[PDB]
Image (cartoon, rainbow, N blue to C red; front, side, top):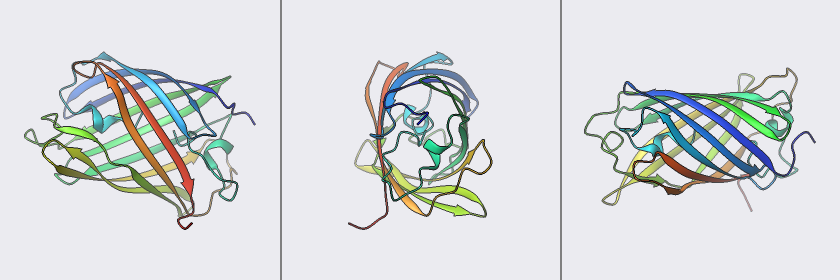
Length: 217
């Protein structure tokens, strides 16, 4: 396999949320076969961010997902040429985000060209007031729609004061090489956590664990 057990991650995100521009660099490592990755993020422009860092974290690669033998692993089969994804995030208070990542590989390193655009967050809402605590663990439903691998998530951020803030995600995934075979319908469970950060989330250590499964025992 082109994909080694230990891989490096280099990332640049450029984005705009409610008109605030930012550039964030990431450096990390992961274990594709164990579905684990960790990365150090550093805000390079636009800091301190005037919105909840949590809305960005799912944009900071389903190659870091433990896939069993009985499910086609589209993501690992996409290398070395790579793949990209496009995602819409719809929040319950009208906030909308569009994100994309183009993922390439050179030697032992995944390179990520990430774009993140968010609009329509109410100024008095939990995102612009920085009242988010974390993403709850979530399940991504994977299926092919009209020849395109699609992942749906229905989830929520936990807020201060025992409240939840609902978000629906739809991601479409496309391999760069024609003829990478599409998988059957399946689930990917993930957990995403900010392990540590400094005062205004200028530096953030991010961790994610993901496991693909078929639903039953």
